[PDB]
Image (cartoon, rainbow over all chains, first blue to last red; front, side, top):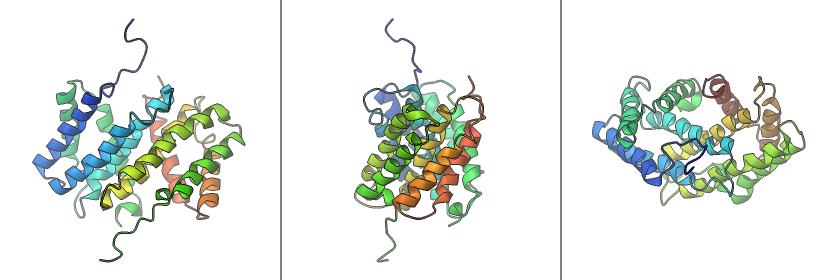
Length: 135
Length: 135
């Protein structure tokens, strides 16, 4: 009936989408693992993807097009940990982000939506293989 | 100092930004591999990244967000082509996408930029083999 066949994600409500970054950045700034100075700059990067979720639909939003926003943000967060870490370990220090992301979902939704938390982790490992990581 | 901040991002230029997608999408329909149905869908996600590249600049550049917007675009194409590549293989079919990309950059800037072509194709390999795709 009301709420038919659709992939009901935690981004179906703008407030829930906001709470995602609202909690996630709170983890980072309170930890200082990447500097609060960077954490709130990350908020804007994430913000961009959040805002575009309501923009990049055109008029009719197809299933394959709807989830296109997923990997865009994921691949961004993967680099975010690297960006403000000039000298360190992108894997050892991303542990706080692994916790942060899952904690954010735990607070925003309560669901173990940690598959997205998995996506970024492997993407990090990929990026560090190219010179773009060390420049 | 004077010169530490320089936007070499081609997608910050209205013509150059459009040229990328404009050449990409047209090269797809001229190929007919993913059909026009796919090409006329791809432009919506790609456009969104172009739009947000105007947003994320805000009032001052930060070196983190400057590169964060790069990977976001590649990821927007990575999964996107996989969707219309549902049939077993994704590599030999995204080959024509690599063609389109190669053609696009060659026309848009004239630079090889196959590093970005590799960027898109590499993320494909990971996601297309994940059990979130084969459901």
